[PDB]
Length: 111
Image 1 (tube, one colour):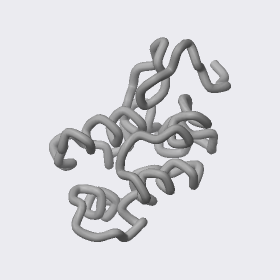
Image 2: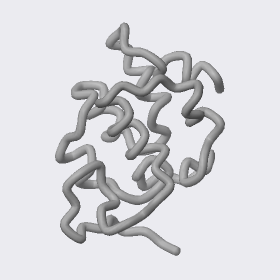
Image 3: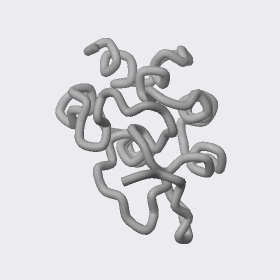
Image 4: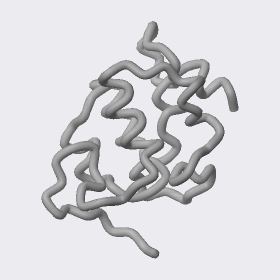
């Protein structure tokens, strides 16, 4: 699984694999990250709750940690830190469950 970090640790190539290892759920998530690398309407509009805010079967427990979301092993740029960590490795769930602007906009989820 360490290959996931090995790709996402740096941005030298346009290979989608770096972002396919970033997000494990809905294609739209790492699709927008592949074309942008930064926040986007669709990137947090259909998202908000799940492994990486996604609506797919939780398998690696991103709500706490996966073993690939280790802060010591993943380099953090300003844009990387905000988008990557908050979307995937965010453990909290407050009034803003999105990457940025969420005026009481909570995506459907179950407790």
